Image (tube, rainbow over all chains, first blue to last red; front, side, top):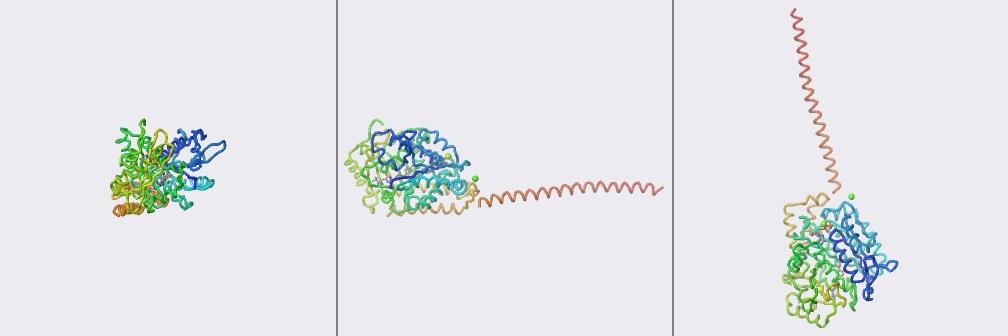
Length: 424
Length: 57
Ligand SMILES: CC(C)(C)c1nc[nH]c1/C=c1\[nH]c(=O)/c(=C/c2cccc(C(=O)c3ccc(F)cc3)c2)[nH]c1=O
Ligand SMILES: Nc1nc2c(ncn2[C@@H]2O[C@H](COP(=O)(O)OP(=O)(O)O)[C@@H](O)[C@H]2O)c(=O)[nH]1
Ligand SMILES: [Ca+2]
Ligand SMILES: [Mg+2]
């Protein structure tokens, strides 16, 4: 288990997905045209996880770019690292999806889905040992939400034994393109509960607040939100992209993070938050990454309990001090970690720091407080759905009101399931 | 179902339109038929006027 196949779908999916390949190509010493110009052998030791090797010693990302309109994928190709992607993997339709799940999942995207799967099969074929798939998308629009979940369901049929992980950006009125986002997100959440092994709940509410309150940016762009996202995307892929005596793949990590199959929605976090000179001490990283203010999903971890936690510290620091600090927060806040999963906080350290920061820490929390996120989208859904508002956009593409009623019920069940383990 | 309903809408728009345009042609022709029939009734009256002058001499 070494190779991962990456898929990015929709405007959002392709935006944050482009930033992921920008950050990690820098970390691995791969330039905009694909050639290696690093110094450490650690940068090439597990480069096969995310890159294929080409003639002339060129490195090409194992990345498939999906969208139902050309716009954003033309911006990817024009952008800084766009030349590195394999041209055959740019798979795109023409008519768009108008922020419509139905268009993505049932009509427009159905016409394009099979040619995306042909490129997946092409990449999966020449993979010594495929460990699984990772996907970047929003749940608020049409393509990434509707088609992205359709792809996830098709990929599971053809590859039922492989791990499916997602970075799924959650919509919020604070950063809102259309009023129908709650509808699209609710329909998508039901898909992820069934068909993904882990889903990283990037909440645009949370990214906005971190940009506004804790970074003092008055008018935050999508780039300021995406800056925070890419820092986390790098962090969660660190232990696969480098050593350091850690013998873990996506499945091994999934096995240790997911105690119940439906409850695989994580609360990501990063320290320090940036947009510095003084490097943080190990105690600061530990307090910040556990702090609610640094959470990428707008939930209060004090309102739930941690099922499992994973933390990956980057930089040259004392592993003794890391152990001490990680043990300090658990033993001084032990009510918020479930007693019925012993030793549920696990940690790793990587010597190579990310670009700019001398030492950082990425937080992966499977907390029952994520019900707050799903309750918020459930409230927005019902506000509109009780008056069948904006439904004509979906019934026009063939959908029934029943499918909405099902999806409403499936997410409220997930909320109830999270509540069960919060009181146990 | 999306195709079925999109086709139904095209079908019934076409049938609703053809029914109105044929119903309109019936109504217009019948309105003009009645106008001429009233005018042709005046020619039959004017023929009786001209006969009752010659049949009174
Ligand atoms: C002992 C220690 C601390 C290492 C540990 N013990 C349990 N856990 C851990 C740590 C991890 N556990 C994970 O499950 C994990 C998941 C992972 C890995 C790779 C990719 C993606 C992913 O969703 C993705 C990323 C970018 C993107 F574009 C789209 C999707 C997730 N990463 C970890 O570092
Ligand atoms: N964080 C972040 N969110 C985005 C970005 N672009 C769009 N969104 C969010 O994604 C949703 C719109 O979906 P989008 O990806 O544009 O639609 P699609 O292209 O049809 O998949 C909204 O909830 C937006 O707030 C981005 O670059 N970054
Ligand atoms: Ca078409
Ligand atoms: Mg958009």
